[PDB]
Image (tube, coloured by chain):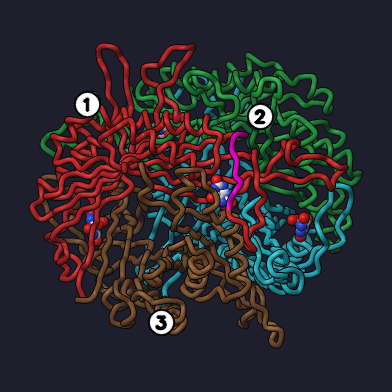
Chain colours: A cyan, B brown, C red, D green
Amino acid sequence: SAVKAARYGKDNVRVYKVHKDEKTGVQTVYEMTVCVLLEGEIETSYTKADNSVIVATDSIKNTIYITAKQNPVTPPELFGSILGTHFIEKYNHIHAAHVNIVCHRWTRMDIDGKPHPHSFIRDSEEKRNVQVDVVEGKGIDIKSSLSGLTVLKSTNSQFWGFLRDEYTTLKETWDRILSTDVDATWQWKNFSGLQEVRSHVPKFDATWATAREVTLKTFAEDNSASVQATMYKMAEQILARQQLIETVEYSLPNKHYFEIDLSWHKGLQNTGKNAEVFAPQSDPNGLIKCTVGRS
Amino acid sequence: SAVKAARYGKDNVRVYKVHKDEKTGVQTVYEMTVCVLLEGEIETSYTKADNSVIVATDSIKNTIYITAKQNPVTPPELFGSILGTHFIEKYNHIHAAHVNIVCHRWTRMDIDGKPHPHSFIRDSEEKRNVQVDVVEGKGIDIKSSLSGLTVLKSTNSQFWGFLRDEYTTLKETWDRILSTDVDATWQWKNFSGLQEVRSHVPKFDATWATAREVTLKTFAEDNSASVQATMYKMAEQILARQQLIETVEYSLPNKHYFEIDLSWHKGLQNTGKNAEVFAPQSDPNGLIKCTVGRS
Amino acid sequence: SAVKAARYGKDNVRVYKVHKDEKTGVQTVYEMTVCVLLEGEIETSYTKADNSVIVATDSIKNTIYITAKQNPVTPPELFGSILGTHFIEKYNHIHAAHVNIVCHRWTRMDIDGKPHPHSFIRDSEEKRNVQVDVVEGKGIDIKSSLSGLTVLKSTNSQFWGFLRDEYTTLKETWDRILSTDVDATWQWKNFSGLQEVRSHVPKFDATWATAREVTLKTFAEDNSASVQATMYKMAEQILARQQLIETVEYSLPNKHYFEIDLSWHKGLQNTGKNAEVFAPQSDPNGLIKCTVGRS
Amino acid sequence: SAVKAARYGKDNVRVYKVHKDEKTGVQTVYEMTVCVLLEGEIETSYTKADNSVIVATDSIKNTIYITAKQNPVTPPELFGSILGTHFIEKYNHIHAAHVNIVCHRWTRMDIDGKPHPHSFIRDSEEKRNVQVDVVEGKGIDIKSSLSGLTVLKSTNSQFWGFLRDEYTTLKETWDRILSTDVDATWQWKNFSGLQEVRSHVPKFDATWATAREVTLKTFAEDNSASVQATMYKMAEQILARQQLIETVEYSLPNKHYFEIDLSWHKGLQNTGKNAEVFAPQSDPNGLIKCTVGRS
Ligand SMILES: O=C1N=C2NC(=O)NC(=O)[C@]2(OO)N1
Ligand SMILES: O=C1N=C2NC(=O)NC(=O)[C@]2(OO)N1
Ligand SMILES: O=C1N=C2NC(=O)NC(=O)[C@]2(OO)N1
Ligand SMILES: O=C1N=C2NC(=O)NC(=O)[C@]2(OO)N1
């Protein structure tokens, strides 16, 4: 037998960083959860009890904190690139570093209509994420995403004209609820190294903001034919607004809200045009995916 | 043996309701999770297999949906009072109804700076809750709360002057992070019935808004001596602003963020005035509680 | 305003302890999560920023570990009593200690049919818990429980003869699935102090074992008229087998499994006597409670 | 722009099935959660609002239940193969079906030492899973796994000889706790279709049982040099015992249990040979992966 694939490292590393402007008093906070997994000439740790090739996961943890102390942690695409580059540069025998970062929201509070210098609210469980793969001789591959953006529209969603056969019970509808948890990922052009990543730094926040804005506006404004048709519109708009993106991926649950027929009770009308009270369904759920690129 | 206490009903009933203004096109959505547990002359269902005394939990579920169809679901204090009153009025042998409602956030989206007529975002996992106990001959007892309001301040929190003995390792501090998940409950004067609840309806939203505003402003502005001292200030302010409240309760975790000494690595300074990178601790956590009333 | 109630302490303290028999080589492990909340003459910490009255939560954490080092951690009723007694004895101004312990399963592995001396499996997420309230001048009040014991029976459950009115849609049944997550609590006679608790130590494990055995056998063997009727039988049997218990409480969800009518598809018969495939319902759920004592 | 990848279907479909032996009275239950995602000539649903190509997710759900009614649900490798084959055979334009099944434990109860005919316990949250990819013209690719198997050993784990540099603080150890949640996956030889899968049916349960037995015995008996070295031994043994497997993958967290130095308190000795009380760490955690194949 032989090792066909191996990677190892530290997961679930919680990290907070504060920036303090001593002149103005304004403080800014960042909070993340980090995973770093390494690949390289490590097979003998598995096959021969050779720990000499292992950079201890505890040391990887230390390195995450040290790197956060010595560098900006934002945008996460940059921080992940710095962190990944460190491992392949420091350790000859390590040839890839896979860095995942989940960024947690700490939005500055407004108190009596003024932004507070050092108080923050977790205004959503929505995350901003990166997956940064630094592979020796193959540059830096970055996938950026937003996830856990939970939305609902109460009308201007439709679903009709789908295939109907002996397995089909679903009624066509011209007016339904649509609710989802948005997971949207944009995949960057390969970067040659850390200089090229740095050269594009403003594009990371700008493209996240575009992706979020497009997602929300398209969801709100599209009189949706299906989840498929709506998500495609989102993806094509994001591609049109950032040429350094190669693909956009969406993964969207269809979180169903069922009508409740109450006509058995005193003739109460709660379906069709009279539908007001619905049963949110926890499971099952539709799950709709696509990856859009340029033609 | 004998039944000393018993209650039963339906838990985890998810409910959505939409309001549609046909004139303006503006739709408004409400989403809840409801629990109704009943008490009364039901002991023989337990002791004698006498199901005749059981209003089926499935029927309780139906009743929740019917009541939501026929009544406003907001404020939740009112909806819970209507729902609880129904069971003690409809069923002679039922003498108490215990209604818990968790209200989920669906905040109207702003698209290109304008409120959208039918699209919403789950802008926080913060909840607004009620616990409405309708007890025959004893009126309606309402506890209102907000929960899951997660906040952090990066300075202007202190903790010194605490007891020090042979069990103490904690260093005094004059500048630390404070983060919590706020659970705040206000307990209303007993109401005699549904007419009295209705007579105070505007006070429910107003008092929730006050509790939230006071919580946030006090957290942000108090140069905190301890969680204890800060939460007391919140409670006393809320009591001062609504005379129909009898008590205010807070339950606050102290979600610790630990300094990370990095001086073992190249003399890096990351403690005290130089502390920038911290380790958020998932557990354990301080837990600080108090109930404040009038003197 | 004034403090009507207050308690504070450390929650979510994870604790592991190992016992090593050096003669035999057999090791035994214990793992818990502990919460200790204190009450006493602490109001000035809330009202006057008086931290002198606060035993720091960090110190409470230290004390949990020290107490575990110096004492048995089993049975949890004893450990909680020792821990709670410590705080009211050590600190004049502390007058109650509220100790909650959740015990996690680490069941010894059998390898090739022989018990292994130092390897364990989490064989269930079922917990054994205690709530120990040590109140100065009022002894030690102990509630013991098992929770998260998830069971299902595929027949020999019935539900008919329940109240039927204009809110009722549920069909009577003489053969259904019954599934629940058992939460069972037995409340001990008040103990005067730690000597009396110690004097009954073997009864704690024995009564937990009885409660579990009775729960499982009654669930399996009772041709159940309702959740109410079955749980009452469990409680009365446990009371009959331990005179130092005063009450037994059950809280049982009815985790519904719905039939699926498939007759619209090629006349497939999947209801009544032909029911084989069911839809487990995540929510809502019945919730059935009772507390049984002696007559 | 163009669709580079797309798949869609129904996730989180809970399914129960009962088998009743009318002769013996013995009933046997199965419970799963199923996901089916389809690929094919579906791009126009995304690009042109063409729903004619969509087999509704609701219909996919119906099909899961119908297929469970008409076929065995065990072993899950077979059920998933039947289910996936159905979609590519029934719908000309569907060219792949991706079926994920999570099997939940319902272990028959023993009551008074005898197996009960119709009562079951969730004896572990450990799962048995399959991932069955049925791809038209490319047969059936099956990955089988066990997950959520949580174990701990209290000694006979070591970690020394790892790389030490300026990022390293971890002390070498010759005696530590090792705890993990086992996720083990075995990848089958490609099967040409459903006849070939059926021809190997007994091997599915047998290989799951082997994987579990090997995992537990190796964990318990290996005086472990590292997680890496132990997991490799597991994988090579499983490969040796089933020639129709091509690879075995493990993904193992190192769930750390930290010593607690208590020497600051009355000289208490709780480290090294005197270590009895430990602090389980919820995060971060090592994460160790490898895929082993034949040479
Ligand atoms: O039943 C279905 N209803 C749906 N709605 C939709 O927008 N697209 C689908 O493909 C569908 O996904 O959930 N299938
Ligand atoms: O160690 C402690 N640190 C704390 N901080 C605080 O504000 N009050 C406490 O009582 C304390 O709660 O967490 N105990
Ligand atoms: O609809 C109901 N079905 C039930 N079954 C039961 O055993 N008792 C109830 O009171 C019931 O609880 O779930 N209500
Ligand atoms: O600090 C470390 N300690 C570990 N133990 C181990 O068995 N292997 C590692 O590579 C290690 O993973 O957790 N890194």
Provide the residue span drawn in magenta: C155-162
In what element is the residue under mark 1?
helix
Left or right: residue A84 versus residue B218 is right
> Label 3's element?
strand
Label 2: element kind: strand
**Residue C237 position within the rendered picture, expressed as x and y whole percent measured from the top left:** 39, 33
Q: Nearer the viewer, residue A281 or C165?
A: C165
Which of discs 1 and 2 lies nearer the camera? The answer is 2
- Judge the density around disc 1: few (<14), some (14-19), many (≥20) Cα neighbours within 10 Å: few
Number of residues whose C-alpha sits closer than 10 Å to that of mark 3, classed few (under 14), some (14–19) or many (20 or more): few
Mark in front: 3 vs 2: 2
**Residue under numbered circle 3:** A114
- Dot 3 and dot 2 within a common chain: no
Which numbered tag is attached to residue D86?
A: none
Identify residue for label 1.
D274
Residue visible at 44% across and 25% down in the picture: D226
Mark 3 → mark 2, Cα distance in angstroms: 56 Å
Residue closest to the eye, A224 or B33: B33
Chain of the residue that carries numbered disc 2 in the rendered image: D
Residue D102 appears left or right of A56: right
The chain letter for the residue carrying disc 3 is: A
Which labelled disc corresponds to residue D144? Answer: 2
Of the 4 image quadrants, the one containing the C terminus of chain B is: bottom left
- Res D99 quadrant in image: top right
Find residue B218 and report its image quarter: bottom left
Q: Are marks 3 and 2 in contact (CB under 8 Å)?
A: no
- Residues at marks 1 and 2, common chain? yes
Q: Is mark 3 within 8 Å of ligand 2?
A: no
Query: Which amino acid type corresponds to the residue marked 2 in the rendered image?
Result: Ser
- Decide whether residue C156 is among the magenta residues: yes
Q: Position of residue B232 (x, y in %)?
A: 25, 70
